[PDB]
Structure formats: C-alpha cells, structure tokens
Picture 1 (cartoon, rainbow, N blue to C red):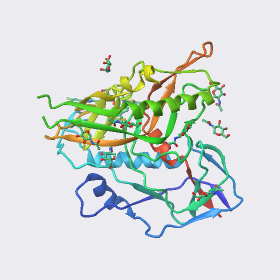
Picture 2 (cartoon, rainbow, N blue to C red; picture 1 turned 90 degrees about the vertical axis):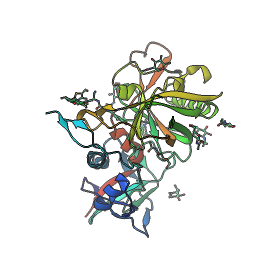
Picture 3 (cartoon, helix red, strand yellow; picture 1 turned 180 degrees about the vertical axis):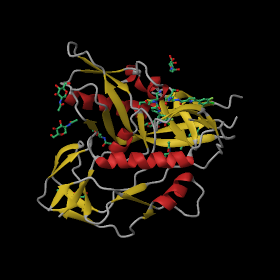
Length: 336
Ligand SMILES: NC[C@H](NC(=O)c1ccc(-c2cc(F)c(Cl)c(F)c2)[nH]1)c1nc(CO)c(CO)s1
Ligand SMILES: NC[C@H](NC(=O)c1ccc(-c2cc(F)c(Cl)c(F)c2)[nH]1)c1nc(CO)c(CO)s1
Ligand SMILES: *[C@@H]1O[C@H](CO)[C@@H](O)[C@H](O)[C@H]1NC(C)=O
Ligand SMILES: *[C@@H]1O[C@H](CO)[C@@H](O)[C@H](O)[C@H]1NC(C)=O
Ligand SMILES: *[C@@H]1O[C@H](CO)[C@@H](O)[C@H](O)[C@H]1NC(C)=O
Ligand SMILES: *[C@@H]1O[C@H](CO)[C@@H](O)[C@H](O)[C@H]1NC(C)=O
Ligand SMILES: *[C@@H]1O[C@H](CO)[C@@H](O)[C@H](O)[C@H]1NC(C)=O
Ligand SMILES: *[C@@H]1O[C@H](CO)[C@@H](O)[C@H](O)[C@H]1NC(C)=O
Ligand SMILES: *[C@@H]1O[C@H](CO)[C@@H](O)[C@H](O)[C@H]1NC(C)=O
Ligand SMILES: *[C@@H]1O[C@H](CO)[C@@H](O)[C@H](O)[C@H]1NC(C)=O
C-alpha cells in the first residue's frame, strides 16, 4: 500500500563525461547514470488519482533547470549592476530522468488519452521517469513527446479563462530557424511548412470544439505583455531567438512555406525571474536549429460568454507549464 507524498528526487542521464556541452557538464556532476535495466511493474486492477497541475515533481525540475542555466548561461551584465564574463558556449539540451530514492516509487498513468487530471485505469510503477529535455520556450513546446492517439487539451479549469491551456499534439510539425552565416548579424528566420501546420491547426480547432460546445474557434495574436510572451522565444545553440508568430495563427487558412521573422536579442528578461541582463553577441556562421513543435500554449479570451465565439491566443511565460506538459503522467507516492 502507498500514500501520496512529496520527496527529494535525484536525476539520471546519459551525460558523456568527456563532453564540453553545458548540459553534459551539468548532468555529469548532478545526475547519476541511467539504469541500464529499468523495471516497470504493471499494477493490476489498480486505479489511481493524478493531478498534473499540482505535482511537486514540476517544482523540482524547475529548481534544477535554474541551477543549470545559472552556471551555464552567464550574462556579461547582471544584478548592484555587475559586469562579468560571458563566454560563448556549447549548448544543446540532453534528456534528464527523475528518480525516487529508497522508500518511494513513481506511479505512471498509461491511459492513451489521459488528460492530466482524474483517475487512470492502467497504472504501473517505475523508479525513474523517461528522458525529459529541459527546453525553455514560450508559445510553442519544442522537442517534447507526442500524445499517443488523439490531440489532448490540458487545463486546470477549462471554463476558467485565466488558467493556461496545454494543447498536446499527436503529430509533430518541424520549425527550422536560421541566422544566416552572412550584413545584420541579428537577423534570423524560421520556416514552417504551411500545408503541415494548417492541417494540424485545424485539428486543434475541431478538438477545441468538443470542449467548447461546438462554438466558433478563433485565433488571434497576443494582445500584449512581455515580448517573451507575445513572441515565440527560445534558445538555439546558446543564442536567444525571438520569433514573430503572427502568420502561425492566421485564421484564413483553417499552402506554402511560412517564414517567420526572428530577432536574436542580447537584453533579455530572465525567465528565472532574476531580472534583465545582457548576454554576449552571437557566434559567427550559420546558427541553425531544427525543432519539432510538439505542443501549444494557449490562453482563452475572457468576456465572450455572450457571443458564440471563443478566442485563443498563444501564451505562456510560466516555464513550469513546460515541465508539466512532460510530467503530467507521473506522481510520487510513499510506501508503508
Ligand atoms: N518583464 C517581466 C519579466 N519577465 C520574464 O522574466 C520572463 C518571462 C518569460 C521569459 C522567457 C522565456 C523564454 F522562453 C526565453 Cl528563451 C527567455 F529568454 C525568457 N522571461 C518578469 N519579472 C518578474 C519578477 O517580479 C515577473 C513575475 O514573476 S515577470
Ligand atoms: N529590480 C528589478 C530588476 N532589475 C534589473 O534587472 C536590472 C537593473 C539594472 C540592470 C542592467 C543594467 C545594464 F547596464 C545592463 Cl547592460 C544590463 F544588462 C542590465 N538590470 C528587473 N527585472 C526585470 C524583468 O525580469 C526588469 C525589466 O527589464 S528590471
Ligand atoms: C497498459 O499500459 C501498457 C504500457 O504502455 C500497455 O502496453 C498496455 O497495452 C496497456 N493496457 C491497457 C489495458 O491499458
Ligand atoms: C480531465 O478528465 C477529468 C476526469 O473526467 C475531468 O474531470 C476534467 O474536467 C478533464 N479536464 C479536461 C481539461 O478535459
Ligand atoms: C490526431 O488526433 C485527431 C483527433 O484530435 C485525429 O483526428 C487525427 O487523426 C490524429 N492524427 C494522428 C496522426 O494520430
Ligand atoms: C472553474 O472556473 C469557473 C469559472 O471561472 C468557476 O465557476 C469554477 O468554480 C472553477 N472551478 C474550480 C474547481 O475552481
Ligand atoms: C532547414 O532550413 C535550412 C535553410 O535555412 C536548410 O538549409 C536546411 O536543409 C533545413 N533543414 C531541414 C532538416 O529541413
Ligand atoms: C508540406 O507537407 C505536406 C504534407 O502535409 C507535403 O505533402 C509537402 O510536400 C510538404 N512541403 C514542404 C515544402 O515541406
Ligand atoms: C509581427 O508581425 C506582424 C506582421 O508583419 C506585425 O504587424 C507586428 O508588428 C509584428 N510584431 C512585432 C512585435 O514586431
Ligand atoms: C530540438 O532538437 C533538435 C534535434 O536534436 C536540436 O538539434 C535542436 O537544437 C533542439 N531545439 C531546441 C530549441 O533545443
């Protein structure tokens, strides 16, 4: 028998001790090696109680990704306004596993269409999660895992427009971002196949209808707020990219290549909440990153319970929701 508990987890990874990349460096001294023979025990006739929006596992990943960025990504000016060293780095996230110490176990929901909250019929017990890459981004969830069957709408409270929505895709759409080798060093662009993106976006529209009484589904650009939230921001090879996602939410098409205009920025608002700092100028050459879009962060407009329209805008900024989208199927329990 077991009870719900919060505990201190430990991480594991396949960090190459030989490597210079900051995530390997970090994982080398912070995580143990992954179990080469991991076990998973199906619990027969067991139904358990999950809640992705209240899982302590998410607060502990957050704490780790902070520690990683604070030792890896050093700005040149920070805080008492300090000026320090900010050397260009090798940067490419690696998968991190989370594991329970003695006397505890992780329970896993295997229901193909589990939404992140409620009971789950097909449960197993494992010692570690799967490998999760700590990808920090807004608007679009990159390089995650995909839903196994249908698209999944996740939200702490659908009818409450203040709660963020996580759309979990079942089909990946590549986004391909380049700061060309050669001139404005800060100009970049992301290409997305519009045929692939618009088909999937229309699948989310029809999915959102099941949950919003077949009311009309409308997308719009974010009304305002932080640059970090009104644009798709993320880190590619150590450079901070800020991309304009207007064309991604073009209701007109719900057929060609979509090119988003992007800006590499040096003055950032730290998602760690540590303020505004200045990073180093970009490395020379073709800065390129190809990522899989595997989810979308949305906020529904308020004040439309009168109309038969429902508007959604790509949002985010709470980086913990990025960790939730991968830990939603797990929860820690204590064994007596
Ligand atoms: N301007 C306000 C400032 N916002 C941020 O720091 C912020 C949010 C999201 C990202 C972000 C996301 C990314 F994906 C990437 Cl790549 C990135 F580089 C940055 N940054 C805040 N300061 C406080 C302290 O009271 C706040 C309340 O908690 S919000
Ligand atoms: N106390 C609030 C906290 N203060 C700072 O961050 C801060 C003070 C001075 C500098 C500074 C000075 C420089 F000369 C250079 Cl070059 C630089 F890079 C940074 N930064 C903030 N947090 C957020 C959102 O995260 C803010 C909105 O920007 S202000
Ligand atoms: C339960 O989950 C396991 C692990 O993914 C899967 O192989 C199996 O098909 C599932 N069975 C049922 C009845 O849900
Ligand atoms: C998830 O499923 C539970 C159990 O049926 C339900 O109570 C909850 O409203 C669902 N949430 C969403 C966002 O569909
Ligand atoms: C994704 O899910 C939708 C339902 O939300 C379904 O119609 C579609 O066929 C699925 N696509 C794939 C590739 O599984
Ligand atoms: C969800 O939101 C609605 C509307 O904001 C509210 O009436 C309801 O109480 C909320 N549910 C919970 C469990 O807080
Ligand atoms: C990504 O786009 C660049 C152009 O910026 C192109 O050279 C490259 O072949 C693309 N990669 C993939 C995998 O499509
Ligand atoms: C875009 O995706 C469609 C499939 O939806 C494919 O048939 C087409 O060749 C793709 N085009 C490009 C330029 O990637
Ligand atoms: C994003 O692109 C649209 C279309 O060109 C433009 O109107 C808007 O001002 C851009 N947003 C920002 C923040 O530059
Ligand atoms: C996503 O994964 C690809 C493939 O490993 C990698 O090349 C790319 O840099 C990753 N993107 C981000 C933003 O981490």
